[PDB]
Image (cartoon, rainbow, N blue to C red; front, side):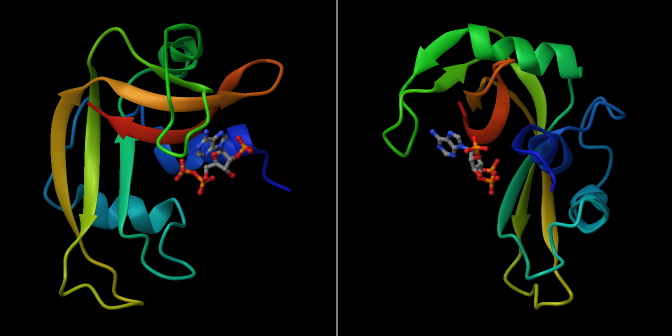
Length: 124
Ligand SMILES: Nc1ncnc2c1ncn2[C@@H]1O[C@H](COP(=O)(O)OP(=O)(O)O)[C@@H](O)[C@H]1OP(=O)(O)O
């Protein structure tokens, strides 16, 4: 089975690119990371930082998760991220996305030993 930590890396980590490279970035990425296999995932965020940097967030600012749990943490510094929003004209299996680059603080939920990121909660 794919572990929770590995799933987070697959759905959210992209250190190979410093920013949202192109307008076609989300269409290629959502497809290659298997996020459109069962249906079109409406929104998803990719983080362009090292794995070490994102893992360190688990020891940063503790904040409440959107779901009410208390295992969420916000990064002290802004990070390069790319938001993918499914455009209305998107129709499974032809999923379509709008690529958007930004620099914001990320909020992730952490779990386990080692305490690592397992879910992307929000960007602020
Ligand atoms: N407070 C929280 N809020 C939301 N999801 C949480 C959470 N704490 C943990 N999760 C995890 O985050 C995963 C997030 O759902 P998902 O795997 O579809 O990812 P994402 O939310 O990043 O798109 C859940 O399977 C759950 O896995 P773990 O139980 O393996 O951590």
